[PDB]
Length: 187
Length: 76
Length: 48
Ligand SMILES: [Zn+2]
Image (cartoon, rainbow over all chains, first blue to last red; front, side, top):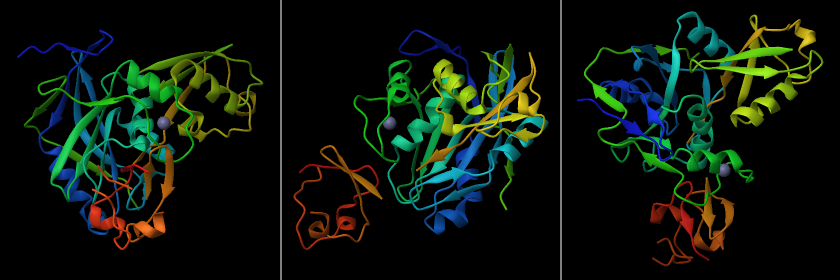
């Protein structure tokens, strides 16, 4: 039951407990968007206890979207919310309403910055028209270095090398049966 | 002087700065140290989101002041 | 949506024809067909 998770570079990763309910509950709350073929994003928020992280809250921030992108718009009000309740950012989640399950260059660039601050940060992608999903992270250090060094123009563009990976099963992410709270800040 | 940038991931970045540094310049330093692009960064001090073209002294940011960093999220 | 042609990036619509785009997709793309027929999506890689 004791897991030791090592990055490519030899760095140990702390455990993140993820409620079993989160993927299902996320798809439920963002369904009106999904049905209008609109991507939606969410934040995985939680707490540090005993050298371990717990995802306690799914937060749906103020955002804009298309069929192929979502993006937050008022991160200051989101900070305010997280700061007041002492919620850490441990990862994020978003939908591919019609696409397969993968991390795009847009998502990779977004997630790199989180993972650089928190080696354990994860990105969950839901592909509900395929009925698939996955939990991803960049290869550490090479994947992160590739994205940090990247200056390629274009919202979407390709990268050389593998860059990212699906988290190991089992891994530092441990899915548990647990309560879950969703906070929808949208207007 | 030094200032601190607390992230929502539980980490605190320390930065050597001058009072006359623009917020833009502070973001570029965060890129140099942490690898986070400036356009993804939003910096907050005492309830105010800080403007790229203004300086630390314009917001009365002082030695050992703590700023807060929140990131733009984008997927798809 | 943006797709890759090995590498150039193209801005396209699912209803754009192969003719309108001008090709293999890991099957050769018939000129009278559209992109959506081949389940082409963002970041799909084509070969010139
Ligand atoms: Zn890139």
